[PDB]
Image (spheres, coloured by chain):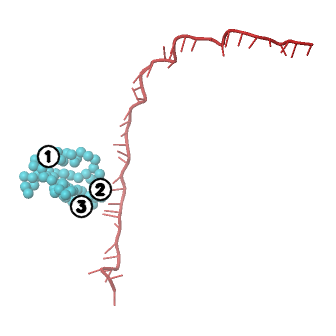
Chain colours: A cyan, B red
Amino acid sequence: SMYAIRKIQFFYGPTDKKSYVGEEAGGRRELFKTRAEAQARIEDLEEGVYYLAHNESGRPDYKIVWVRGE
RNA sequence: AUUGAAACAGGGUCAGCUUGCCGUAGGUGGCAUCGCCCUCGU
């Protein structure tokens, strides 16, 4: 259906929270038809240096997911 | 008898481990400072 990415973020202190990708801006969460686009998207996020926020434990984990077509 | 009274952004985390400005290339070739006059006049 609609392929996309699940986003998880681990903070120091056992807590941690979840949100998709594409919730940054006016555009809603972004939708890819093919898993290949999602794989490339994962790669290009993994490419760069990662700048930690405050009270952040380690580099985030992305996993791939297809969401039922909205 | 104040929608008041009490209310830590806290606890730590190397910018690091390294690389030749090198190998050469001319200040040369060459033109007379010359041609000339009193120290006399007692």
Q: How far separated are the C-alphas under marks 2 and 1?
A: 27 Å
Q: In this view, does B42 lie above or below A19?
A: above
Q: In this view, does A38 lie above or below A19?
A: above
Q: Looking at the picture, how far across and down is residue A48, in whole percent?
A: 26, 46
Residue mark closest to the camera, 3 vs 2: 2
Q: Which of the marked residues, 3 or 1, is nearer the chain's N terminus?
A: 3
- The residue indicated by pointer 1 is A37
Q: Which of the marked residues, 3 or 2, is nearer the chain's N terminus?
A: 3
Q: Are marks 2 and 1 on the same chain?
A: yes
Which residue is located at x 10 percent, y 49 percent?
A: A33
From the viewer's perspective, tell me whether residue B28 is left or right of residue B18: right
- Count of picture labels: 3
Residue mark closest to the camera, 2 vs 1: 1
The amino acid pointed to by label 2 is Ala
Q: Which chain carries label 2?
A: A
Q: Residue A57 carries which label?
A: none
Q: Mark 3 lies on which chain?
A: A
The amino acid pointed to by label 1 is Glu
Q: How far separated are the C-alphas under marks 3 and 2?
A: 15 Å
Front-most of residues B24 and A13: B24
Which residue is located at x 19 percent, y 58 percent?
A: A26
- The residue indicated by pointer 2 is A53
From the viewer's perspective, tell me whether residue B10 is left or right of residue B28: left
Task: Tell me if label 2 and label 1 are in contact, CB under 8 Å.
Answer: no
- The residue indicated by pointer 3 is A15
Q: Which of the marked residues, 2 or 1, is nearer the chain's N terminus?
A: 1
Q: In this view, does B41 lie above or below A30?
A: above
Judging from the image, what secondary structure is the residue with disc 1 in? helix
The amino acid pointed to by label 3 is Thr
Residue mark closest to the camera, 3 vs 1: 1
